Image (cartoon, rainbow, N blue to C red; front, side, top):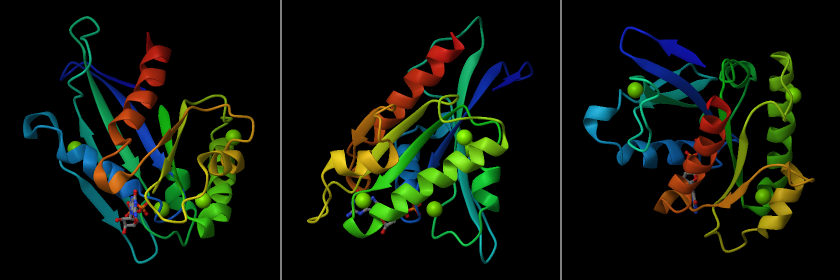
Length: 192
Ligand SMILES: Nc1nc2c(ncn2[C@@H]2O[C@H](COP(=O)(O)OP(=O)(O)O)[C@@H](O)[C@H]2O)c(=O)[nH]1
Ligand SMILES: [Mg+2]
Ligand SMILES: [Mg+2]
Ligand SMILES: [Mg+2]
Ligand SMILES: [Mg+2]
């Protein structure tokens, strides 16, 4: 949401949210691997025993100058199993858009629903509803042999089909850029 006169940049924050081990890191790292060195900052991981945050910023090469001003995307996620809520609540501060990385595993179906309820709860602390922020659903791990039907996964996190849904196999980069383009489209629309 930030404007930075000094370096001539507007800054958008994109949060990858979802149950633990759904593929959030993997999305971030695939993306970070295809950005040229000169257009990205460092990928940074801050951790305690119980908590983690991982983030980087980059200048997408797909985006026009809004009157001399470049666009910088900052991608944030709370990777790993989650022990406390505090890093997931904080991750959402000043969020512009969110990718929800759902796990296609039968035994993570409940974890999907749980993380979505939690995102909704954390958003509510900032006075925001699920209608107030662009949210895209990525159904990741479509390669698993017992991958649930996409419609089933979608049904527990988005029963009225309010959000765009994309399939992914983040370990192979599949769906990864298309998911980032989708949230990008919605965030940049709101801007202009
Ligand atoms: N089979 C499969 N494994 C995946 C996929 N995406 C991520 N993983 C694996 O899932 C585990 C958790 O992924 P990670 O990105 O670290 O999770 P997160 O950051 O906690 O959401 C890792 O072992 C990944 O290799 C996928 O599309 N298919
Ligand atoms: Mg996590
Ligand atoms: Mg950076
Ligand atoms: Mg599932
Ligand atoms: Mg809410």
